[PDB]
Amino acid sequence: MIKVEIKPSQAQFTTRSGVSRQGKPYSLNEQLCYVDLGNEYPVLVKLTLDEGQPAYAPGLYTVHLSSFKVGQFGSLMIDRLRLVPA
Amino acid sequence: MIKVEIKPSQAQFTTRSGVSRQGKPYSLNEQLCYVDLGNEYPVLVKLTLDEGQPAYAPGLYTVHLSSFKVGQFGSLMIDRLRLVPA
């Protein structure tokens, strides 16, 4: 299990916006977190939230299986990092 | 934890080869496996092995932390799926 932490300073999201190729509006909500990759300190990672989801509250989390998909070359990839409480 | 299984029929690797942009030879060893992504059946996934590593033997495995890296846009990505015995 991957340990992910939302620090107190990371409790909000920001929103970026634009227009798709054929005219549709979009909005993306982004939140920061720390992921422990086994180095001397955790590293900073950007999360893009799913539609209608609030920012994750401060605390400890692990990664949900729905984060993964098989990519177009047949290898496993991360689609979007989706979290669940630890 | 991600459940990965090497079936008896997947106990070997194949090798692809070529030459890099500035003349260096390379060889890549590839092995297949099944990864349970929570659908009705596990899905087929291609693994690229690291230099000097044998094919994983048949059995159950989970994913090592070294599989992950922060990508050039700041989000988490899979570098290469690296496995450890379950």
Image (spheres, coloured by chain):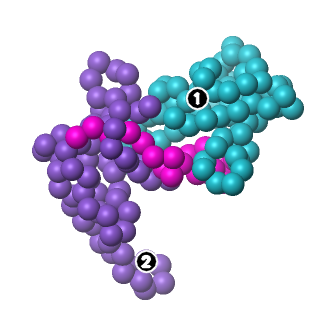
Chain colours: A cyan, B purple
Residue B51 vertical placement versus B6 (above, below): below
Report the span colored magenta.
B59-78
Give the side of residue B57 with respect to residue B85, left or right. left
Residue that protrudes farthest toward the top in the picture: A52
| Residue B18 position within the rendered picture, expressed as x and y whole percent measured from the top left | 33, 75
The mark found on residue B16 in the picture is none
Residue under the point 34% across and 21% down: B39
Between marks 2 and 1 in the image, the one whose residue lies nearer the viewer: 1
Query: In x, y percent, where is residue A20?
Result: 67, 32
Please tell me the numbered disc located at residue A62.
1
Task: Read off the residue under disc 2.
Answer: B20
At label 2, the amino acid type is Ser
Residue type indicated by callout 1? Thr
Q: Looking at the image, which residue sits at the far left?
A: B9
Q: Is residue B3 left or right of residue B12?
A: right
Within 10 angstroms of label 2, few (less than 14), some, or many (20 or more) residues? few
Which SS class for mark 2? loop
Question: Residue drawn at (36%, 75%), measured in percent from left and top?
Answer: B26
Q: Identify which residue, B50 or A5, lies in the foreground.
A: A5
Is B50 situated above or below A15?
A: below
